[PDB]
Image 1 (cartoon, protein in one colour):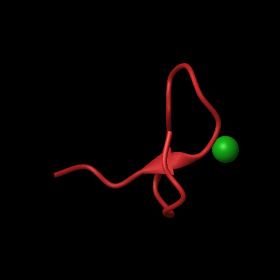
Image 2: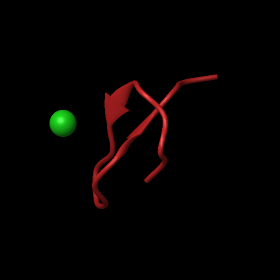
Image 3: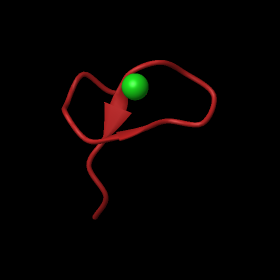
Image 4: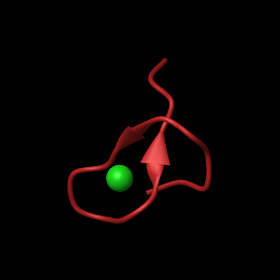
Length: 19
Ligand SMILES: [Cl-]
């Protein structure tokens, strides 16, 4: 659910950085 690199999100495309 974000534009950043990181882990895939559960329910939306895009990724997130934990923390
Ligand atoms: Cl992915």
